[PDB]
Length: 171
Length: 171
Length: 171
Ligand SMILES: [Cl-]
Ligand SMILES: [Cl-]
Ligand SMILES: [Cl-]
Ligand SMILES: [Cl-]
Ligand SMILES: [Cl-]
Ligand SMILES: [Cl-]
Image (cartoon, rainbow over all chains, first blue to last red; front, side, top):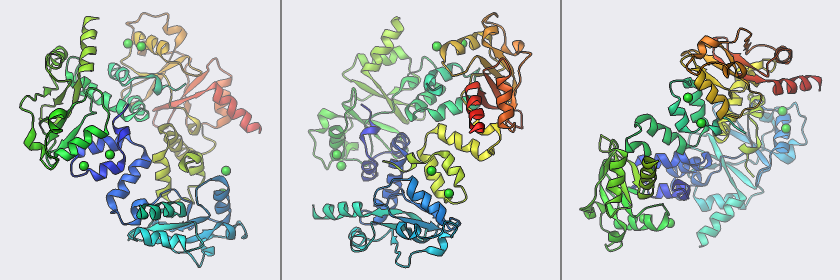
């Protein structure tokens, strides 16, 4: 019957003018790392920025990875709305996307940096929720990467999440 | 069948002369945040100081909150022995207590800082266990706030806990 | 159906050339402290060093402890392959081992530092896996302490673990 188990990170954000920082910190310490992550996003991104609903869970590899690593990633992990994998450089800058279907057609020794999809777009974290939902919905993608204003890949948004956003903005 | 799951934070305190700090730290890292909190209190407050049995779980709001926030706090959280809410300033200094019964009689736009109970007492963390138990038992309160020697609200003690303390000091 | 719940700390190590540090850090933050410990060992010790398979779970006391503490440790904790307890100085340097059977024959007021077993060996963390397994198997011990190159007791290896290592190095 616990207290901090009864408050969401969103509650904390919404009540940031009224709760002592001490209380917020004890709440954060008692929550899951996933919930702390949600709090940091809500704290950085306002209610109509897609950054706020970004999911850090994703398939990502550095620009040193090969087809062999990508194939193994897709085979070893089960993830909702996933059929792409994101490539970053050593400063975490998003470089591009490789697709599952294409990467099972290449040789395993091939660097992923040489097989980046020509179609691949990323959302900026400041994109509006409805522009985000449109961008995923009217494409052939089931997820899109999200980058911050420094170019760093911070996470992804899924087609499933876009559906929620839309249905929210009806109700 | 785990080891650090078999040792309480109290065990660690009691054995602080005999366990390497390295062992204590690994134990603390493996425990829940609630258990780490218990350890810090036992580490700071000796066996006959009420600080040691202080509960950080409480209804608290800053002096910027209104009746509207207080009403919503009481309605959204279920907490043992709770019918008061504590107001602190921006340096976390305890200012006073508002009671549930009174705050459901005021207008929601009213600042809590203007409705502090005249009756409201706080225990100092160094109060003896039996003086603490008496103070809660022979009052009309079911909980009291505890402050440190800097004036900061560090937590509360409940009527239920006081009962335990008493029954302990019989046995 | 979570992602970081699907990757072991060993996976992370094996894929350290290919995952962004950002991804590794989020994975580590989401895992248990035990799993983070496993990662630090794999990160420090290579595949044929016993340090890598060291268990931090152990009975250890400082050189200020008495027989009374040791007796109580053995009686209050259930631990796999355990019938020894390790004594360290205040800088965590391994000094020696006391055995359960012997310490139940001494007076409780006696300092453990005066009852160190003459037989007691420790493995260096760089010992090969098969030399480690041999050392435990062909002795009268069911566990051995492991020390780092600074002399610090970092953990233990059990007879059970040695069996695994052997059976691994067959298959
Ligand atoms: Cl691989
Ligand atoms: Cl695998
Ligand atoms: Cl409110
Ligand atoms: Cl609510
Ligand atoms: Cl003892
Ligand atoms: Cl005990």
